[PDB]
Image (cartoon, rainbow, N blue to C red; front, side):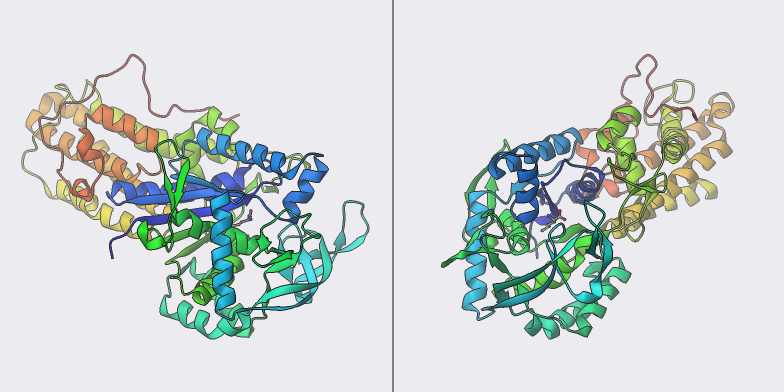
Amino acid sequence: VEKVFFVTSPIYYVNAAPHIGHVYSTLITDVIGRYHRVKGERVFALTGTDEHGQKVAEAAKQKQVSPYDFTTAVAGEFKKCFEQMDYSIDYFIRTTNEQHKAVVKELWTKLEQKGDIYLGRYEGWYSISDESFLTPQNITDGVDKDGNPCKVSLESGHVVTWVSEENYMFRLSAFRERLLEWYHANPGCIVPEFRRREVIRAVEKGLPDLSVSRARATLHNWAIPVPGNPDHCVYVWLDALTNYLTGSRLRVDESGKEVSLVDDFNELERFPADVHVIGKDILKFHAIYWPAFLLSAGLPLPKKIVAHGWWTKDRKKISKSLGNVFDPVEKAEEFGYDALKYFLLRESGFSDDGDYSDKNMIARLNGELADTLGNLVMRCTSAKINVNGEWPSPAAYTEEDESLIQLIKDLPGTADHYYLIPDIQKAIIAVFDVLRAINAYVTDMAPWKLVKTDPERLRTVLYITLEGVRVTTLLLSPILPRKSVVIFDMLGVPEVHRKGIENFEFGAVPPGTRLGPAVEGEVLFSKRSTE
Ligand code: MET
């Protein structure tokens, strides 16, 4: 089936200013989308803010201003942050959006008409901070804003409160068997595999029904009224997850504003999501609740959920209160935007909780970006080595030559598979293995000596090196969007050859193609010292 490739980030709570986690989640969403665009597919990448709920309402009361004003301000900080980060997200959705509210009421009504919503009670623990229902097994003793004996979440250490309310209940218990068939029928639907095994384990045990409304007073009336019952507000998470459906139904003008909400998702060809990017902390909502609502509603399920780990800086937890900040915009202004993105995507894979340090950041920048990639691009474009500033016509290939060409021919297929898992770390590693090999070959052939000893041999070496750099750069273009463009400009690659699977093939740029012009004292990535 040919559709718009639909990739999403979570929509983030606006209780506080944007930080590394949100930037990271959205970066992953952005990269996946960028990769599919270079394959020449239609893409719709979505991000946004989760604006209702007790959490956010209470954060706005502590700042002493109205929820409308608070949400709008912090939403503006998220937008500015994501604009500053230089993503290519197609739409930014806000749950306060009036068209989103409409979609929630449709979905709610669908679940009701299906017989999957009844009036009951929830008597149990709740984490306001995580907007999450918890069982006694998932709580323990801790301390509060005072240092008094309270209870807290085992998942996140946030304070939990006991809740005893008449609530509308969704019949989650009835979807155990269908969710299990879904996980087994699609054994790559949740990534990484161990997180997938976690979900199955939990659903195997049993599922209780889920509260999907709350008494209106508890939410400080900052939520979507339940259709036909204004005493209840819709569960912030049922509201939030619906953003994926809403976004799938919004037509967006060139400027980025929503102009229209279609009746049927099939109209825009986006739903269901091909990949939901999320953090491990919200897996249950996406892998258990969401598919269950969708099955209830008769809507198609997503194809993949990819769930990633948390970040630390210098092996310490990130918190401005604890005196350990990690400002991405600041670190990007220092070391470069593409470099920072590279590091975040290279340093840790999804199954791990990565660790930033200035030490390790400078090591990768210098080692991989400058010494391996940058160095190689300057060599094959240098006036010393490439005396005509053109793509030379290759002569006969040696066996060594071919060993390298084979690695390059194989690289796209391999990088492709990793991008589609998705496993961006392994895609990057694959590309740089090929880059290390090209460097080894260039050291080995010593083209600088060939300039005078064997010009005919130089043509071959130089052509392979150029083509290896082009192909590796193309495949890195979702990771280094701006730098890939500089590289292609230096290689003088025509625009048409900078995307499309046609240009994954070795030899797509003809000999005779002219290099771009040099600039006095230019460098791709410049090295930073070890303080
Ligand atoms: C439907 S994704 C909701 C995610 C939630 N607002 C968070 O910040 O964790």
